[PDB]
Image (spheres, coloured by chain):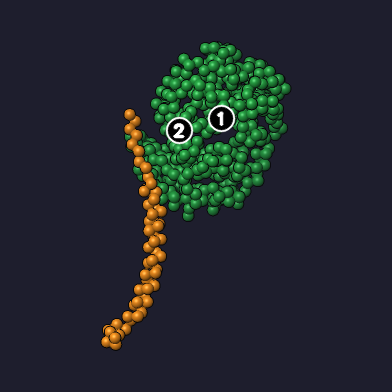
């Protein structure tokens, strides 16, 4: 595969600058930060989201629309996102523009300016959208599959936070989150595409060299009944192994075996925890039959796998998790997480080796370890009266 | 005592059955109740909340 290895050179502050040169002419230079809603302490539950809104509204060097203007003029796309564990600010731009794609990113992580005036507006923006964020039923289901599964922990609370905090937030608080969770050893400068690693390392030395230097799963159930909705969304999960756990790969193959309606499957991983399960949307009348169907399948893998199907699963995984030339953005993203989670970029050859070592016996062993006789977390929203209660799903978790 | 004996040749035996019976129910009831309380705890802990969209 002649994979372009990801050369990662570290910095004094610890930016762990990394890179994976590629022929593509445009590149994606991003900053990842190990800071999410898991690091918030319920008094600043929307600080990362609201800082993610404020981060493009001007820094000392780029007051007002300067930031957006320049990153617009250069012709680059500026994006940012926040999860429960990671925050990313990345720019897709013509490689030659690295010089500015990097200096701009430096401002966004440090020297940022949180104009109180702007703060006011972003508050309104976040709040109002949240007032409508309820339209994204799936996100709702998935932010309760989190609340009821991680009750009492910082992993239950959402990325956006409760409207309460959103309204009650001030520059100083933000400043704290910014000055507390934006440390240089918890930061990765990732570059993918037409970039040279030595030039990127010199730019990180020139700019960004200033950056300062028991989660538990609770088998439970939340049922939001609202019978006026046309469709019902139900998510059932168990405790995922984690990000670093080796068995994650044998679980991905299991998901590739499974693949009523919109019956997706997810393996969300956080630092030594996670949610492994399925989300499906169905007319109310069929919710119970779906559930029965789904539980039977998990059970099928646990006791009755087949090399053929495993193969089907290994192959789909193989065509997946490539993140290679899939594009600068995706690749950079993967590197961004790989340096934050694993501490290194796992190459695709190692992924292929870990895929080909998976057989049917260890797949049903790992599935029995993680699915069989486990207490799930259930989150339902919509006409969910025929959704079975916890004893029936409890009993369907075993044969 | 004898006339009693004839009227119930199993006075003793019935009483042996009653002893073991007591013991058996004595172990089954508490346990069954416990289970009754496992499978009913789920509901007995259910917390309902009304959230009109308001």
The chain under label 1 reads: A
Q: Nearer the viewer, mark 2 or mark 1?
A: 1
A82 in relation to A352, above or below: above
Q: CA distance from mark 2 to mark 1?
A: 20 Å
Of residues A239 and B29, which is closer to you in this image? B29
User: How crowded is the residue under tag 2: few (<14 C-alpha within 10 Å), some, or many (20+)?
Assistant: few
Left or right of A169 on screen, residue A228: left
Residue A383 seen in the current view: no
Q: Residue at x 52, y 39 (%)?
A: A266
A293 in relation to A199, above or below: below
Determine the image quadrant of residue A269: top right
Of residues A325 and A391, which is closer to you in this image? A391
Q: Position of residue B22 (x, y in %)?
A: 37, 70
Chain A, colour shown: green
Of residues A42 and A344, which is closer to you in this image? A42
The chain under label 2 reads: A
User: How crowded is the residue under tag 1: few (<14 C-alpha within 10 Å), some, or many (20+)?
Assistant: many
**Secondary element at tag 2:** helix
Q: Residue at x 41, y 27 (%)?
A: A164
Q: Residue at x 58, y 19 (%)?
A: A108
Q: How many marks?
A: 2
Q: Residue at x 50, y 32 (%)?
A: A41
Instruction: Check disc 1 and report the residue beneath it.
Output: A35
Mark 2 or 1 closer to N-term? 1
A25 in relation to A73, above or below: below
Residue A10 seen in the current view: yes
Instruction: Check disc 2 and report the residue beneath it.
Output: A139
Of residues A140 and A17, which is closer to you in this image? A17
Colour orange, chain: B
Q: Quadrant of the N terminus of chain A?
A: top right
């Amino acid at each position: 595969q002649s994979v372009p290895e990801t050369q990662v050179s570290i910095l004094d502050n610890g930016l762990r600058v990394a890179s994976e040169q590629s022929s593509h002419a445009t590149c994606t230079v991003g900053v990842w930060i190990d800071a999410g809603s898991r690091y918030e302490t319920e008094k600043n539950n929307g600080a990362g989201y609201f800082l993610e809104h404020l981060a493009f509204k001007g820094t000392k060097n780029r007051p007002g629309n300067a930031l957006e203007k320049e990153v617009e003029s250069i012709g680059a796309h500026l994006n940012a996102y926040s999860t429960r564990e990671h925050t990313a600010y990345l720019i897709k731009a013509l490689s030659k523009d690295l010089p500015k794609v990097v200096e701009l990113l430096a401002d966004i992580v440090q020297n940022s300016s949180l104009e109180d005036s702007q703060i006011e507006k972003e508050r309104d923006v976040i709040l109002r959208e949240m007032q409508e964020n309820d339209a994204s039923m799936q996100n709702v289901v998935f932010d309760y599959l989190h609340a009821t599964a991680f009750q009492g922990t910082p992993l239950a609370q959402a990325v956006e936070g409760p409207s309460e905090n959103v309204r009650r937030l001030s520059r100083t608080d933000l400043t704290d989150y910014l000055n507390r969770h934006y440390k240089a050893p918890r930061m990765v400068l990732a570059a993918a595409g037409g970039v040279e690693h030595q030039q990127l390392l010199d730019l990180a030395q020139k700019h960004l060299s200033s950056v300062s230097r028991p989660c538990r799963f609770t088998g439970s159930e939340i049922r939001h009944r609202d019978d006026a909705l046309p469709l019902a969304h139900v998510a059932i999960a168990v405790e995922g192994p984690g990000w670093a756990n080796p068995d994650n790969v044998t679980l991905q193959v299991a998901n590739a075996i499974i693949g009523c309606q919109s019956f997706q499957t997810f393996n969300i991983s956080y630092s030594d925890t996670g949610l492994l399960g399925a989300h499906f949307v169905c007319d109310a009348m069929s919710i119970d039959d779906m559930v029965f169907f789904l539980q039977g399948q998990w059970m099928r893998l646990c006791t009755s796998a087949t090399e053929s199907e495993v193969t089907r699963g290994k192959n789909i995984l193989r065509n997946a998790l490539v993140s290679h030339l899939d594009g600068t953005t995706p690749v950079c993203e993967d590197i961004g997480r790989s340096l934050l989670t694993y501490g290194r970029r796992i190459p695709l050859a190692e992924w292929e080796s870990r895929i080909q070592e998976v057989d049917a016996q260890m797949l049903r062993d790992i599935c029995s370890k993680y699915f069989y006789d486990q207490c799930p977390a259930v989150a339902g929203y919509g006409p969910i009266e025929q959704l079975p209660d916890y004893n029936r799903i409890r009993s369907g978790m075993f044969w | 005592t004898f006339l009693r004996w004839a009227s119930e040749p199993e006075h003793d035996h019935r009483k042996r059955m009653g002893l073991k019976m007591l013991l058996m129910m004595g172990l089954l009831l508490p346990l069954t109740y416990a289970m009754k309380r496992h499978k009913w705890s789920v509901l007995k802990s259910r917390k309902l909340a009304y959230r009109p969209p308001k």
